[PDB]
Image: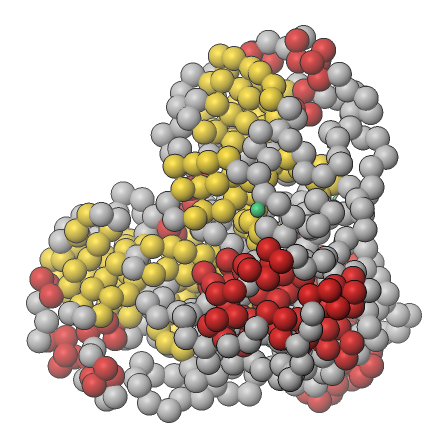
Amino acid sequence: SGFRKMAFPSGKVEGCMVQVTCGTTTLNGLWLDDVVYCPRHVICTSEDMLNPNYEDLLIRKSNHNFLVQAGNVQLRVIGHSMQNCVLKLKVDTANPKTPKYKFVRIQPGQTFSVLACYNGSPSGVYQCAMRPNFTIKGSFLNGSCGSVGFNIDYDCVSFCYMHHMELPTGVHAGTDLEGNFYGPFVDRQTAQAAGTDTTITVNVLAWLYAAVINGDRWFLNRFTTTLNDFNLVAMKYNYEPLTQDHVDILGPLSAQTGIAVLDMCASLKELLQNGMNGRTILGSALLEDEFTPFDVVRQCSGVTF
Amino acid sequence: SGFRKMAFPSGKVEGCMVQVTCGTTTLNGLWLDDVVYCPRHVICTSEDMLNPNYEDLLIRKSNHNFLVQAGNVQLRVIGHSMQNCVLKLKVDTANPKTPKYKFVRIQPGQTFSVLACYNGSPSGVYQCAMRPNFTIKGSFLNGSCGSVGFNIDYDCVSFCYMHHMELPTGVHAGTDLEGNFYGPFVDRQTAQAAGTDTTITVNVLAWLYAAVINGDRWFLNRFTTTLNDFNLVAMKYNYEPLTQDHVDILGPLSAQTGIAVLDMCASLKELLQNGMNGRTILGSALLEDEFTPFDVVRQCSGVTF
Ligand SMILES: CS(=O)(=O)Oc1ccc2c(NC(=O)Cc3cccc(Cl)c3)cncc2c1
Ligand SMILES: [Cl-]
């Protein structure tokens, strides 16, 4: 029993965190096999950041311009290349702590653990979701660039995010491990704004199913809805549209609790109209959207209370 | 920017998690040097739990009755003893991954990271506080017994909790690493209830300072109060008393934001008698009490491990 926002154990990832220095700039890199991955903006000055020509800045660099530090050991850089917005530094030693890994690009609504690092040293781990506007609501300070987001499904680490920048509203933007940004963002200090954010509807529904499994039923009602009527109402509250794919994904939780997805959708429409009335759901006074349907099944028991 | 509930990197602890089997029971153990620590109830059947005589049950066991598994390796048990509610199993091999460690007993209000394990395998990491009623609001399933709570002090791991049981309300009870329970609980299948819980006041104040640092100032007011006047309000809303020690501990956050502790207390006083009025603080509609003053300074300064 109990439901917590839970991150994956960060051990396999901590053993990959290195410090990357290029001139006066210092950020974090990810050491996998004989390659160190880091944001390509490590080669820029603050004066270059407005309109950088990364290809032109990179061609002017040599392997000895990059200082890579793993704990108290200097790693020797023997090659450098760029893949989209990520810089790949070939080193002379394969990381003996390299876990079984994959590079995965995630869709909005998906969750992951972030190992926040400063100077190649892990300082904290937290759980978060890729927002529908492609930003992440992280907790990042100066020097956190290069920190990674991951999922550890079974014994394999799947890397899905690398931190690059903070937008003016305090939210964060980054890339997958192939250097492709999530969202309409660029690694430039030009004016960039995150689009209007919305609530991840399928995730709130999954969290309502988790509350039912944990014994909370006060919000349930005798109503059901069409999928279209649910969307007309939910979109008025800045909720993401619920697709037929989302309904299918909630199928196992619906089977386990005995509450059809469109029946749970009717509880949600009521919650958005009535508020909580001083009540809480799983210790929260807001509807929680950073738990996917897969997270709920993984965390929760197979017997409803 | 950003403020998240963040756990310590779990790496140093994951390297200590082992599986302990005694007959039909399987739970987790902590392997430090040549000793494996686990709950003493691992030696009990379900009938034994009703009223156990642990010394009598233990004297009937031999070293070969305990199966200890570290990854895919069988550890040889060469001795067994009991310290309060923890069983200590002497093994032939010292853990090569043993970090620098301490065993510490924490006070209610202090926070820690929990590495939830099943079959000696870490599956999740979350942050939580020792409640004033000595229970922890964890997220635990069957087989999580023996999972540990910890903090990191520079490069030293401070072990403060070992999971033993779940109370009927879904909250959890456990011991320090010396086998001494937190709270008026016993390791026995019998009726046990958690006392009425209170809010950790100094922690809410620290979380209000974190909101100010992050730009949330709507709750600030021109007013100030006294420790006497405030503690009358605190008693009335089931809040823990605020001591002069708590005021001193909040000193650095007070200096950084320019809001005196009794000035922040008058904001908390108003939040209790009037509510949030549809507003949120750090994305929350409730006053958060699971972040200590040290946690806030650490997350707003970028301390690494
Ligand atoms: C005082 S503060 O604002 O919280 O400190 C920061 C500073 C930089 C932060 C940072 N790095 C950048 O945004 C630098 C940058 C600039 C323009 C383009 C690009 Cl691709 C990168 C990432 N995360 C949190 C950050 C907090
Ligand atoms: Cl995805």
